[PDB]
Amino acid sequence: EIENPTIAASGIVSVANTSDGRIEVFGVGGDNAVWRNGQTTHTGASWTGWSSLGGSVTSKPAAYLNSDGRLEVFVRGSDNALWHNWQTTPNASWSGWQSLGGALTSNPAVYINADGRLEVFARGLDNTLWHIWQTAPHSNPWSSWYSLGHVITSNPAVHINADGRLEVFARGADNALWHIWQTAPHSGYWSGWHSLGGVLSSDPVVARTVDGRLEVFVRAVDNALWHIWQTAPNSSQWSNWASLGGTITSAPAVIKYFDNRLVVFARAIDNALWHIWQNDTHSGSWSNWGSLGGGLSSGPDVVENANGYIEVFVRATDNALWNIKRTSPSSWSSWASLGGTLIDASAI
Amino acid sequence: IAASGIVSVANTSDGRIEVFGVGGDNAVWRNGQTTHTGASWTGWSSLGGSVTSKPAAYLNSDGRLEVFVRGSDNALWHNWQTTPNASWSGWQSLGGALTSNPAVYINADGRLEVFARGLDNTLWHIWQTAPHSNPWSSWYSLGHVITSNPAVHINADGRLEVFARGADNALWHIWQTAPHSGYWSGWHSLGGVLSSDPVVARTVDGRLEVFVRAVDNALWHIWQTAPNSSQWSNWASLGGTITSAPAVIKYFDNRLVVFARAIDNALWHIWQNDTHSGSWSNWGSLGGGLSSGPDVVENANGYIEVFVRATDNALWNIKRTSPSSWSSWASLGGTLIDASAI
Ligand SMILES: CO[C@@H]1O[C@@H](C)[C@@H](O)[C@@H](O)[C@@H]1O
Ligand SMILES: CO[C@@H]1O[C@@H](C)[C@@H](O)[C@@H](O)[C@@H]1O
Ligand SMILES: CO[C@@H]1O[C@@H](C)[C@@H](O)[C@@H](O)[C@@H]1O
Ligand SMILES: CO[C@@H]1O[C@@H](C)[C@@H](O)[C@@H](O)[C@@H]1O
Ligand SMILES: CO[C@@H]1O[C@@H](C)[C@@H](O)[C@@H](O)[C@@H]1O
Ligand SMILES: CO[C@@H]1O[C@@H](C)[C@@H](O)[C@@H](O)[C@@H]1O
Ligand SMILES: CO[C@@H]1O[C@@H](C)[C@@H](O)[C@@H](O)[C@@H]1O
Ligand SMILES: CO[C@@H]1O[C@@H](C)[C@@H](O)[C@@H](O)[C@@H]1O
């Protein structure tokens, strides 16, 4: 069996914007339960503190905002089935845990189709890519499970093309970046598999540029941040792999700045939070790596807050969730503890 | 009503502004940024047709632009990209008998839905039967009597909500009972005395806010007190003496910015100082000589772009170029007419 390098450490929480402009974070507690924390209001003046959604889980959770404004959380259960939990009205009471069945061997990843139906992707018992979907927009019930085939050796990553076609990425048995896409938006058909090559030592992490090009970030076997991109929207042509250097020890976290420039965050060999950023959205010019310090026991996860500024979440050495955020166009916040005790329940 | 904007302004799925106006021949003409940097424009191309309303462009969730306009026969007509950012379909009739500009929004299920005043002066609507696809429903009346072009937005919970001035010149609104539920609410009055179309934004914290010119020619606004709120604020005056429909857009930090032509026919703007206190700036001039209201969009650099017709009847452009700077006033040329149906 081709040997697959250990994937870079995952982030500690699923970070989601609510329909009322607040950050909500979902992590796994010492009791194996999903625990939640969120801003009291969109100004982010304070947080609610940790409350338990309960359950007993065996993956990193994945939260997603339905097109009717209700958050929904996906996780692999004690039984290796997919379980989910939804707000019953926006930013209100939670449903409790419902089984969607299956036999999963990775974290679940979620995206929304061009018709408002959520669709979840996970490695199945046979190590092929599996998927499942809402049968109606922002609503139960769900399909049964289907295999898209292949052999994958990482958690899958999912995004949507400029033309509304979902596209999923994973490391293959050969360590290359593999991907597959809907033939047209929720057409009922997928394209078959394409290798982008490379030798990955992390999950793929996918953004769409403001001009509509998918761009994928990975740690490679040299422990550098590498990336690769569509040459145009929906393009039949990808770039060559290009190194951004560094010695990173986490999955990269990617977000567009308020001016749409890509910014990548990762833990480095010194256990600090580091970041590197586009100088512009076309020429392909990137900055040098800048440290933001801290002592990280996980990868970062990132969201844009209601002030239009980047917020970053990590687990610290005290196993609490820590937060650092932009406070203006020209300044970072102080490191602050949001407390809690979080375990890394990442499935791979 | 207060003078309308001259163009429908829409972002493409490949991060370029496209503008759609009516030429002196009554055809729909379009102009686009050559790339997402917005450094240059293609120049004007004709989509043809003979039109009797302002066009309304909208991006389908499959990334294809689509333009809606009232035809010579007062029916709704539409023209769509057959693939994203490529060739146009030409003009197809969706029938009906319309007495206003069409306004368009996308449902939580990816179906476009078009609102216009009908032959009996009630609110009419029509929708795609499947997401981002033909064919369309037949026409249905949601009733009432309206005296302005309708405006449409979506609540934080995915319910479409439509705004129109009534025969009392008050702001009226009606909403889906739930996202694309098949049912709508009763008509409700938010009062006031409007002298323009309503223009609607949704705040970053998920509250609908409506801007109007009032009978005193001042900018006024009213807002939901909370997302999906069963309670709105009182009307509040932002003052000024404006001679166009206002145009509203969130800044990169989500502060609302409102643009309007003033009595001096210059482009003026006023903005929130923050998104939690109801505190607004003073009016600031950006100058120009305007023969229309402004239309606004956020470009692929994440900055506000503004489009107005000038005294020469050309389309002019001013935009933010950074966190700290405006662009030059640039002429995109052409000759545009105001084909607004009301
Ligand atoms: C705030 O509560 C603390 O953090 C949670 C995430 C859980 O690990 C819990 O057992 C612990 O007591
Ligand atoms: C509430 O149910 C508990 O949590 C779920 C997420 C599943 O792991 C299930 O097996 C377990 O009993
Ligand atoms: C109904 O869901 C649609 O059809 C299924 C058969 C799958 O192809 C899925 O990716 C797609 O969104
Ligand atoms: C149709 O799908 C498009 O072309 C394919 C050949 C791939 O390059 C894919 O990334 C892209 O989305
Ligand atoms: C560029 O062409 C000019 O502007 C167009 C919008 C039309 O009004 C046309 O008749 C005129 O010649
Ligand atoms: C292309 O067809 C022309 O333009 C349409 C928008 C309609 O006004 C129609 O009656 C006219 O003949
Ligand atoms: C299918 O379309 C849905 O049902 C129709 C009967 C209308 O109520 C419409 O607003 C809604 O989007
Ligand atoms: C259910 O609809 C909500 O409550 C209504 C009574 C109105 O305030 C409306 O703006 C809002 O969307």
Image: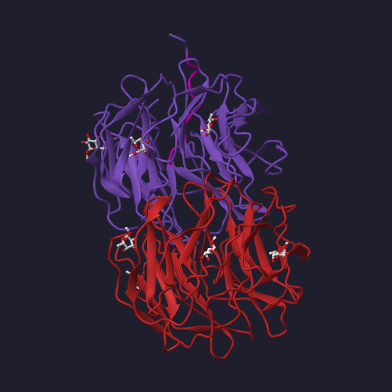
Chain colours: A purple, B red
* Residue at screen point 49% across, 59% down: B78
Image quadrant in which you'd find residue B257 = bottom right
| Number of numbered discs on residues | 0
* Residue that lies at the very extreme toward the bottom in this rendered image: B216
> What is the magenta range?
A4-13
Expressed as whole percent of the image width and height from the top left, the position of residue B324 reads 73, 61
Residue drawn at (30%, 69%) of the image: B184
Q: Where is residue B194 in the image (x, y as percent from the top left)?
A: 50, 85
Residue A10 is one of the magenta-drawn residues? yes
Is B165 located above or below residue A289 in the figure? below
Question: Where's the C terminus of chain A, which quadrant?
Answer: top left
Quarter of the view holding residue A82: top left
In the image, A241 versus B188, the foreground residue is B188
Q: Which of A39 and B240 is in front in this view?
A: B240
Main secondary structure found in the magenta portion = loop
Residue B298 percent across, percent down from the top left: 61, 59
In percent of width and height, residue A321 lies at 45, 43
* Quadrant housing the N terminus of chain A: top left
At 48% across and 68% down in the image, what residue appears?
A: B102
**Residue B227 in sight in this render:** no
Please name whichever residue, A309 or B76, is drawn nearer the observer in this view of the structure: B76
Verify whether residue A285 appears in magenta.
no
